[PDB]
Image 1 (cartoon, rainbow, N blue to C red):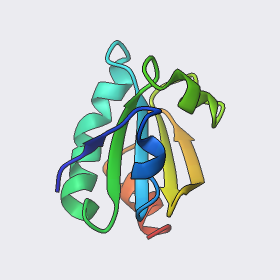
Image 2: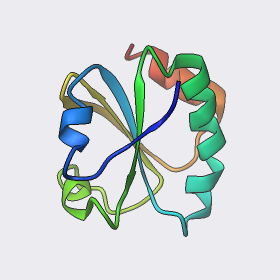
Image 3: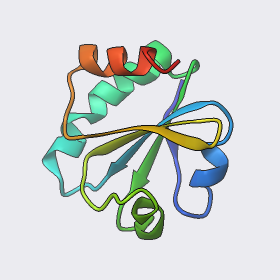
Image 4: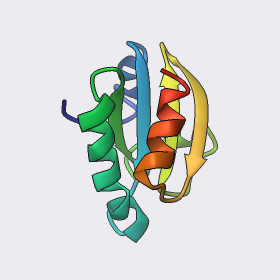
Length: 104
């Protein structure tokens, strides 16, 4: 549908409504921009079955620290308010949609 944005202020509310993938990112990191169209493919293919939330590590430094994240791109998967998976680096579409469909 459309990808969401959050910070420490609201990431906890956003992750507490369904299956929610998150992308801990920063714009100076090449791989964060390389995985962006792959996340848009997931938003087209599954972005109603799950939510996708962009979250920037400079802005949510505390919240990323809540999961020991201080490196990017770092994907998280949360479900009804709790983390259930974490992954780091770029991924191709097929692997990412396989990873997602396993936790729908």
